[PDB]
Length: 49
Length: 49
Image (cartoon, rainbow over the protein chains, first blue to last red):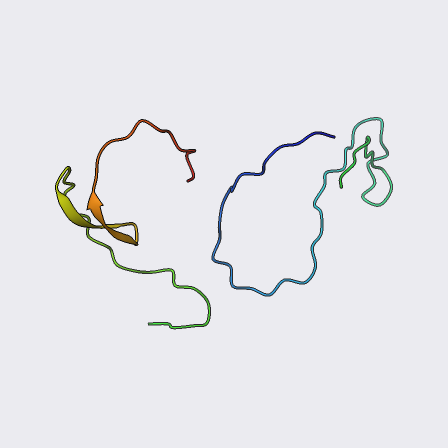
């Protein structure tokens, strides 16, 4: 909780039609993970609203 | 040359002209129009206003 304003950042002339969106997010891998593209991955923890 | 329902992207260029002050003049700033006297001012805007 708290209060703050949102600034304008950028404006783009993209006259497309929009209906859906997807969040793009990184998956971690290391010597600890199996590294398999389907299952050898670590997310850590993250949250969005 | 393409004309479309989408916005324009190629234009101009526009011509700028010399500034003048204290006289009563017609002014055309960035597509804003009016008449009056222009003078320097103390107040500061935000950088996007």
